[PDB]
Image 1 (cartoon, rainbow, N blue to C red):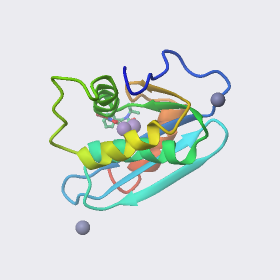
Image 2: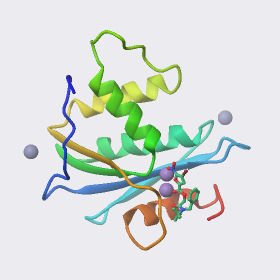
Image 3: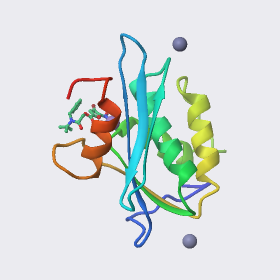
Length: 146
Ligand SMILES: CC(C)(C)N(Cc1ccccc1)C(=O)COC(=O)c1cc(Br)c([N+](=O)[O-])o1
Ligand SMILES: [Mn+2]
Ligand SMILES: [Mn+2]
Ligand SMILES: [Zn+2]
Ligand SMILES: [Zn+2]
């Protein structure tokens, strides 16, 4: 957009973080984390959270733990949309910042502009044995039935 350009296609060669978050509304308990194609993984447990917050928190962890070039695969359309819109509309007319999750998205943006290249893509969550499926099992354990 303006303060940054996300990549149009995955960065060839760069580590890929399959991120996910899961939360339970009745208890506000959740988990967020990632598995990568270089054999990394991390799961953090969270309190006082929401599904959308956990999806964003997982992106934050991926940005925190990655190098200067990073591929991130999320299944959260919200997470991808609010981050991309923030990048496309900064210091530009017509922009009111969101009324929810604003502090967490600001933390993500501050991590993002530190990077050299970021590819961020949405996949519908799906069944199988791939990356999105693995991190989903990890963050859903004890949080939601699969
Ligand atoms: C995809 C499949 C088919 C293996 N499931 C089962 C499942 C699908 C949809 C909702 C709950 C569980 C998962 O992977 C786990 O669900 C997620 O990951 C998930 C759902 C949604 Br909605 C989001 N999201 O907006 O981040 O993530
Ligand atoms: Mn998810
Ligand atoms: Mn998932
Ligand atoms: Zn609490
Ligand atoms: Zn580089």
